[PDB]
Length: 99
Length: 99
Ligand SMILES: CCC(CC)CN(C[C@@H](O)[C@H](Cc1cc(F)cc(F)c1)NC(=O)O[C@H]1CO[C@H]2OCC[C@H]21)S(=O)(=O)c1ccc([C@@H](C)O)cc1
Image (cartoon, rainbow over all chains, first blue to last red; front, side, top):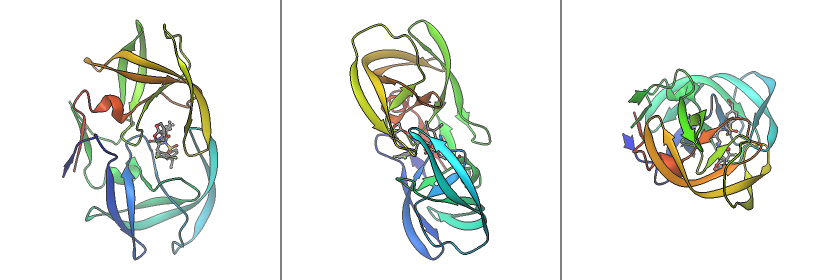
C-alpha cells in the first residue's frame, strides 16, 4: 500500500501471537514496542528521543508481521508511548518515502 | 524522488535564509528544529516524545523549502536531538509511504 500522511501512519502488526497497532516511523532507526512478554534472550540497552531516554530490553531475531508483510530483526521492548516500526524493519517490507 | 530507508532520510531545507539538514519523519505530527534564530513572535509550548517532554518556541506560518519543495506551516524550535520534518509539512510537499 501507498499511505498518505494526513493521519498518523498506523498499521496492524502481529508479534508473539499478539495483535497491535504501530506507527510506521521513518524517524526511528530501530523498532520500539510498548512493554510485552517477547520470548527470547535479551540484553539491556538505553535509547533516547525527544525529552530524554528510556530503558529497553533488546531482543534480536524477532518475527513481526507488518501489515501482512513478514520481517525479522531486532525489537526493543520498553516504556515507549507508542509502538514504533523503525527503519531496521521498514527496509525488509520494502517501504519507501515518495514525493 | 523516491527514498529508501537503508540510511536516515535526511534532506536539505532552507528556512530563514539558513541551510539545514532535517529528517523526514513520518512518526512526527509536527516539525521540530534544533535551536536556531527565527524572526517573529512565538508562543511557548510543550511537546512530548520517548523520553518525556521539552519546552519549545512555536513559530507559525513559517516558510520552509524542503528538498526544493516549498511549504508554509508551524515550526517548533527547541532542544530536539535532531531536526525533524513532521507530517504537518510532509503532507504539503506530497510525501507518501509506499510498500
Ligand atoms: C526527534 C526524535 C527522533 C530522532 C532523534 C527519534 N524518534 C522517532 C520519532 O519519529 C518520534 C516517534 C514518536 C511518536 C509518538 F507519538 C510518541 C513518541 F514517544 C515517539 N517522534 C517524536 O518524538 O515526535 C515528536 C515531534 O512530533 C510529536 O508527535 C509525535 C511525538 C512528538 S523516537 O521515537 O524518540 C526513537 C525511535 C527509535 C529509537 C531507536 C530504537 O533507534 C530511538 C528514538
